[PDB]
Length: 224
Ligand SMILES: [Cl-]
Ligand SMILES: [Cl-]
Ligand SMILES: [Cl-]
Image (cartoon, rainbow, N blue to C red; front, side):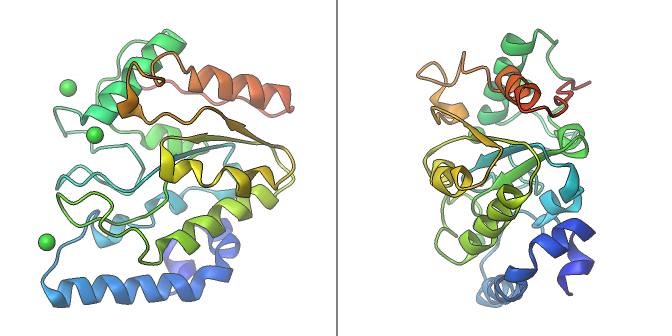
């Protein structure tokens, strides 16, 4: 299927330079199935981060690659489906920081769809993974896709705040710094860094301060 059928209209335009690379990744994914290998998330969720309006994105949260545990990854970085439990450790850690930073109670489930519908892009640098093998699809060609997404956002006039969780994420810092009105939160601890840099990092309140500072509206981070 062509790009415009896979993603939201603004995203289809922003990602038009990687239309060929997206088609090539679809061929890669068919070949993994033909070879007897599995991948996560489900085919229909791979590009799910780009099915919310491009024009509305004000915060970018970037992880490394999807959860490697079958049934966890749903196409939105760090999220899980509402009936998934226990939460993955990364997500439990994020939620601890959510409560500490903002003062809100613990969420009722692990579904970050509300963030996405409010203009947070929940991006992973690499958009698929082989089950139980983290970083197994690193260097297979998703990087050109996600680099294009990040450069297209950085090219807009509009304010953007980036939150880069981990080493793979943090490679995007110089691509982001190239744009005007782009602020990047540093340093770049992963939620699994836990008490060695992640807890107390205040990502959510910092994002909002930086957005207001740049004249944009803040994010409503509230989860039910
Ligand atoms: Cl497999
Ligand atoms: Cl839990
Ligand atoms: Cl995890």
